[PDB]
Length: 142
Length: 141
Ligand SMILES: Nc1ncnc2c1ncn2[C@@H]1O[C@H](COP(=O)(O)OP(=O)(O)OP(=O)(O)O)[C@@H](O)[C@H]1O
Ligand SMILES: Nc1ncnc2c1ncn2[C@@H]1O[C@H](COP(=O)(O)OP(=O)(O)OP(=O)(O)O)[C@@H](O)[C@H]1O
Ligand SMILES: Nc1ncnc2c1ncn2[C@@H]1O[C@H](COP(=O)(O)OP(=O)(O)OP(=O)(O)O)[C@@H](O)[C@H]1O
Ligand SMILES: Nc1ncnc2c1ncn2[C@@H]1O[C@H](COP(=O)(O)OP(=O)(O)OP(=O)(O)O)[C@@H](O)[C@H]1O
Ligand SMILES: [Zn+2]
Ligand SMILES: [Zn+2]
Ligand SMILES: [Zn+2]
Ligand SMILES: [Zn+2]
Image 1 (tube, rainbow over the protein chains, first blue to last red):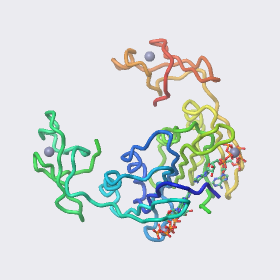
Image 2: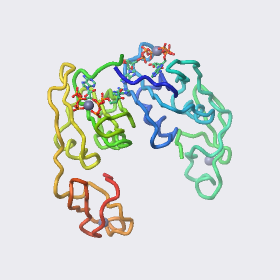
Image 3: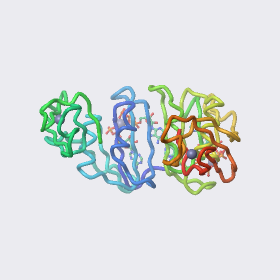
Image 4: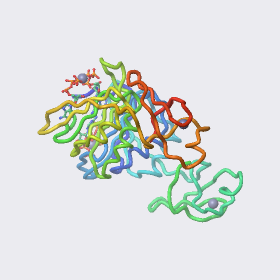
């Protein structure tokens, strides 16, 4: 019924309604061919989102960023139209820049100091700002 | 192969890379099931985007908004899994506010002034701001 990917990545089992957030964070080149399924059937999740990206094999850094958005996705490496590998995003121990400290008065939001964070818990996800040492109350990609 | 739309809308022939902007302006309910194809083959346009929405038949207002973003779209109404009607957008001659002038120096972008544009050409689409007289370099709501 539709053009099957030859070479690329299929980010499957994304929590329903979060594919657009994931896609934005990945920030792929403008001419990239992509298929985005939102709120579609899932035997495992009931409903889910899917991101199919042609011609790109995500780098570790991008892969792991996804873990901060949807903790149970399956990264499917496609080659010759076949799934040759399934990866799970890793929640990093530390993060450079990337996120916004949710403390309005943090030195990183008042001065020119790049963000720095540390993950202190994976489930639930708890991220502490290195500088003000306050936990983020939300995950925000800068 | 993939699940088809049973009842809803298939917005076809969207200019490549513009489906997300179109989807954003439609602002559909959070639980809406959707399929977005970006930069896919098209005999008619070489490359294009396609937006498929289950459970929603776009209202005229939305239809005409889409055209400003992508003038050659085809609105396909789906019922019982079949395209029962093929709609073409109507491009207005004038526009009140709605769009943001793409000229940073325009008064509308420095003071709180209600935008106003004139469509001087639909093929190709040329939208002129009444205040600064400059043509939009992009359709922004
Ligand atoms: N070449 C391809 N082009 C586009 N989509 C593909 C391709 N290969 C498989 N997929 C997608 O990758 C995902 C996983 O494929 P498979 O690994 O075939 O699913 P499962 O359903 O067998 O995997 P899970 O058991 O879901 O990991 C599915 O969502 C599938 O539609
Ligand atoms: N390119 C696509 N366009 C439209 N719908 C799609 C596309 N690819 C996958 N789907 C739909 O996504 C749903 C899940 O397919 P898969 O992901 O194939 O189910 P599973 O049952 O393999 O998923 P679980 O592994 O159950 O999440 C199906 O309804 C399928 O038709
Ligand atoms: N029930 C459906 N579910 C999902 N997609 C559909 C469904 N019916 C048809 N479409 C899509 O709607 C668009 C128009 O269908 P048709 O009108 O069948 O295509 P054409 O290619 O025959 O139309 P054009 O000649 O492209 O207007 C196509 O992109 C088609 O794949
Ligand atoms: N849900 C989908 N998932 C992935 N790819 C899709 C999906 N629906 C359609 N496509 C792709 O969109 C492209 C155009 O299909 P159609 O829209 O069927 O072509 P046309 O030749 O009918 O288009 P024109 O009418 O030529 O734009 C094809 O490559 C098709 O496989
Ligand atoms: Zn599956
Ligand atoms: Zn801080
Ligand atoms: Zn067609
Ligand atoms: Zn202006």
